[PDB]
Amino acid sequence: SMNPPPPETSNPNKPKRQTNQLQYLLRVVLKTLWKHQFAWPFQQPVDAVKLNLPDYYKIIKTPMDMGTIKKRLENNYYWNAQECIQDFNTMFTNCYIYNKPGDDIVLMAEALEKLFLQKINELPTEE
Ligand SMILES: Cc1noc(C)c1-c1cc(O)cc(CN2CCC(F)(F)CC2)c1
Image (cartoon, rainbow, N blue to C red; front, side, top):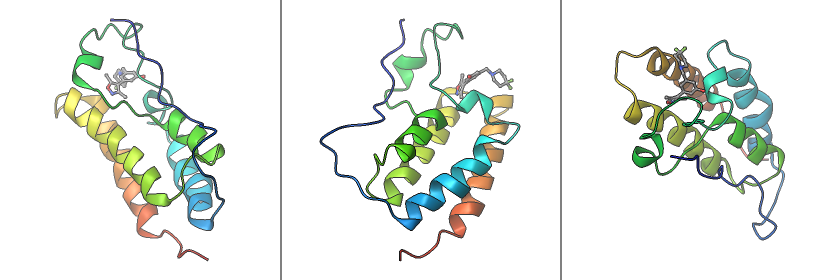
């Protein structure tokens, strides 16, 4: 169970724009979660080899992580905020699907998700 390639973070064919909602997602939302004490397991793709999780990529077919999200934001990969929000949701859902409801990693993801929802509650209107 080698790891898959990471999710793409740039694509020369995918259209680009800089907007204030995407800026908010990078500067406020991602920033807040990134620097949180629970961020670190989520700051890069799950390395199922180093973590000895041979079934991870049998269960999780749409991996996602904040490192990927950060690069996507930095690279103007997203056209709109919803695309980015979807990736955060994917990351949290994967964690909840793969792990058991007691688990420390799940509590960590719940805390980040609560914070995520607070910051997305205040997304600015598009200029
Ligand atoms: C995210 C994610 N989703 O599913 C898995 C499995 C991971 C995961 C990713 C990591 O980079 C490291 C660990 C180990 N874990 C960290 C927190 C802890 F609470 F300390 C327990 C050990 C788990």
